[PDB]
Length: 58
Image (tube, rainbow, N blue to C red; front, top):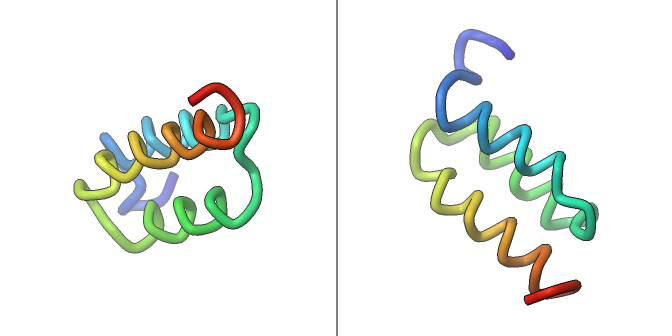
């Protein structure tokens, strides 16, 4: 997206939107973190995905 939203950040962004059973506050938090943080967020991406899994298939 912008001059920030590059490598891991965008892959993760996409994968994040791609979550089929995670959409609330977690989605929000992850968008926010994707927006402020460069590379730590990928670990956190794995977290968003596991959250998706936590509500639905863990």
